[PDB]
Image (cartoon, helix red, strand yellow):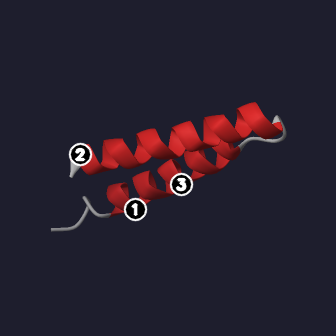
């Protein structure tokens, strides 16, 4: 599970960085960070219960 969460993050961040290198506009890294934060919120809401 941790390996999958790491590989997906590594591929997404590299794709966003390639997009930044090419276009040079805005930041898909913001989208990656937002997705990570949403996943973190879901995880943190799933540990308070049994």
- Crowding at dot 3, Cα within 10 Å, few <14 / some 14-19 / many 20+, comes out as few
Q: From the viewer's perspective, is the residue at label 1 or at label 3 nearer?
A: 3
Q: Nearer the viewer, residue 18 or 6?
A: 18
Q: Quadrant of residue 14?
A: top right
Question: Gap between marks 2 and 1, in whole Å?
Answer: 16 Å
- The x, y position of residue 6, in whole percent, is 33, 42
Mark number displayed over residue 10: none
How far across and down, in percent of the image, does residue 31 sit?
Answer: 64, 50
Task: Tell me the tag on residue 35.
Answer: 3
N-term-proximal mark, 2 vs 3: 2
| Residue designated by label 1 | 42
Residue in view at x 65 percent, y 36 percent: 18
- Number of numbered markers: 3
Identity of the residue drawn at 58% across and 43% down: 15
Q: Residues within 10 Å of mark 1 (few under 14, many from 20)?
A: few
Mark drawn on residue 2:
2
SS label for mark 1 = helix
Report the front residue among 31 and 10: 10
Instruction: Give the percent coordinates (x, y) of residue 20.
Output: 73, 36
Q: CA distance from mark 1 to mark 3?
A: 11 Å
Identified at 15% across, 68% down, the residue is 50
Q: In which quadrant of the rendered view does residue 2 lie?
A: top left
Q: Secondary structure at mark 3?
A: helix
Looking at the rendered structure, the secondary structure element under dot 2 is helix
């Amino acid at each position: 599970v941790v390996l999958s969460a790491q590989i997906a993050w590594s591929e997404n961040v590299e794709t966003a960085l390639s997009s930044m290198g090419g276009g040079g506009d805005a930041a898909p890294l913001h989208s990656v960070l937002s997705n990570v934060e949403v996943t973190l919120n879901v995880l943190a809401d799933s540990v308070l219960m049994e």
